[PDB]
Amino acid sequence: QWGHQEVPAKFNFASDVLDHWADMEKAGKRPPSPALWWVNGKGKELMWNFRELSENSQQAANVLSGACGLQRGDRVAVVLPRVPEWWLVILGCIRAGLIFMPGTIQMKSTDILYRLQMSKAKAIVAGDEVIQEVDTVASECPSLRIKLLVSEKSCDGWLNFKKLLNEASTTHHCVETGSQEASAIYFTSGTSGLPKMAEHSYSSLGLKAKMDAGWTGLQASDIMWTISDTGWILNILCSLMEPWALGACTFVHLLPKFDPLVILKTLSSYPIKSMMGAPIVYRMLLQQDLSSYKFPHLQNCVTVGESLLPETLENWRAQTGLDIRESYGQTETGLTCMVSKTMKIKPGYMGTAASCYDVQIIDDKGNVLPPGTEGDIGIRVKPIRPIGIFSGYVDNPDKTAANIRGDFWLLGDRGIKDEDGYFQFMGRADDIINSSGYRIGPSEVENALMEHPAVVETAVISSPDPVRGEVVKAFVVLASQFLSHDPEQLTKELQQHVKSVTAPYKYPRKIEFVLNLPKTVTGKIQRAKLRDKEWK
Ligand SMILES: Nc1ncnc2c1ncn2[C@@H]1O[C@H](COP(=O)(O)OP(=O)(O)OP(=O)(O)O)[C@@H](O)[C@H]1O
Ligand SMILES: [Cl-]
Ligand SMILES: [Cl-]
Ligand SMILES: [Mg+2]
Ligand SMILES: [Mg+2]
């Protein structure tokens, strides 16, 4: 339905990338080099060089294939905190030809159930903080056969990973996995609807990562700290595959409370040269006392996930002397556009295409648009599907086919490309409002509302109108002190306020006051959920 690939028949990140570095150490061609440095922020630290990482990951593969009896192709849910065993287990899965399916420890039992059922997981790997949740729902998951516990303690019904690991052989015969063979399944965030199962192959993660490696400016002798939930695709790409493609060290902090002061102390206390985090990390750091906590070793700061505001960029540069280089992507496509270390930074832009990709702005018929014209961001997938693109939605070929327009995979995001090929994000396409022939981006309206002291949080969406077709509607969470005000009067005041700072065709003709907004587990506002209910 979407091009053929040009790839080697076989590919495996463990054998083709990681084991190279272990072999160099074994052969005396490189000194023993740190690969994984883990700290808990309470005095415990652990470090593996590449040889040790290879050996201990071979033990993990033996545990999974031997003791757990998991066979090539079997699906393994992984729900762990930021502990070194996540890295070991994922590598174990890659070696043993098992499909790893990471998720967040922040899941409720209902979330865990949905994913285990939908995914037909045959195994779950978890820590002691989620086993009680798992054990309330496990009987309802008929494919689930193995429960593997990473803990200092044992629990009846759960296999003891750490004990089995120490018992296992340090030799494992890596499976000769195919480049297009399924390696992972990631659920999408659920921002627009129920989470989708996105299948990735050995090459779409590992070979793509190998091709991208170094875009951050990270080099072989350096340490990168990627700040991420272990359930996100960011973790596999930037915490695991990209440093290890280069022979560099990945730094992991348990960071049990995402505390920005702990982040700051960590930067200032360890020789971290490169860091990756969502824009909120930088925003939080800027609210800390950066006079008192210097980090002269830090060189490269990158971000992904939401728009990097120009003010954030400017403030960071002023306070630290450093740039923040933005990137863009989605579960389905991995790293799609970025500002590489040699590129000029353009505030408000997310960079240029990843090297495997032909990224364009396209019209409603799939035609490439000139620079300066807003349209849909797409990646060319015909006649050749590029390395890095996912394999499709599991059990949902129709949904896969629905996002292909002509020769392009649609990201679902609007954008504009400038004269140098840099992309500017212009919003989720489905969120743009069409009222009286005007297109209205909710972000500008939400920003105008957030200026007003009454507004704590807001979401702007379309609402159906006996006709203007649809109108702009704002859902507003009020500051406590405004709950007492007359709402009709306050509504007019907020309307007038927006009319004062934006094109007055953009103002919310409807305002509904609400006590909360629906969000994903990561805190992303579910505008679709609101739109769906608004439209019945
Ligand atoms: N640099 C960025 N600037 C603006 N938005 C970004 C950037 N990076 C990513 N995004 C947004 O995040 C999206 C990808 O997020 P992800 O794949 O986690 O799932 P999601 O789309 O939020 O959830 P779902 O697919 O279930 O609706 C992109 O399609 C885009 O809307
Ligand atoms: Cl913390
Ligand atoms: Cl920002
Ligand atoms: Mg999405
Ligand atoms: Mg406000």
Image (cartoon, rainbow, N blue to C red):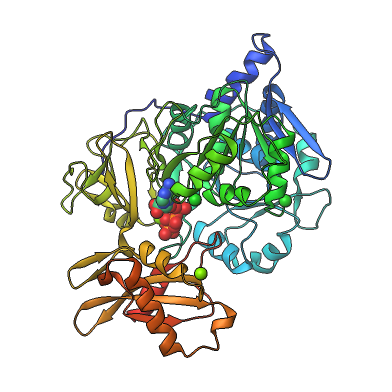
Residue drawn at x 57%, y 58% is: 143
Residue drawn at x 69%, y 43% is: 264
Residue drawn at x 55%, y 85% is: 483
Task: Specify the farthest residue to the front.
Answer: 500
User: Residue 209 at x, y = what percent?
Assistant: 47, 32
| Nearer-the-camera pick, 112 or 157 | 112
| Nearer-the-camera pick, 448 or 28 | 448
User: Residue 355 at x, y = what percent?
Assistant: 36, 30
* Viewer can see residue 231: no
- Compared to residue 532, the image places residue 320 above or below, namely above
Residue drawn at x 37%, y 43% is: 349
User: Residue 156 at x, y = what percent?
Assistant: 80, 58
* Viewer can see residue 129: yes
Question: How many marks do you count on the picture?
Answer: 0
Judge left or right: residue 452 versus residue 263: left
Task: Specify the farthest residue to the top.
Answer: 28
Quarter of the image holding residue 49? top right
| Nearer-the-camera pick, 190 or 491 | 491
Judge left or right: residue 184 versus residue 264: left
- Compared to residue 141, the image places residue 61 above or below, namely above
Which quadrant holds the C terminus?
Answer: bottom left
User: Residue 283 at x, y = what percent?
Assistant: 56, 51
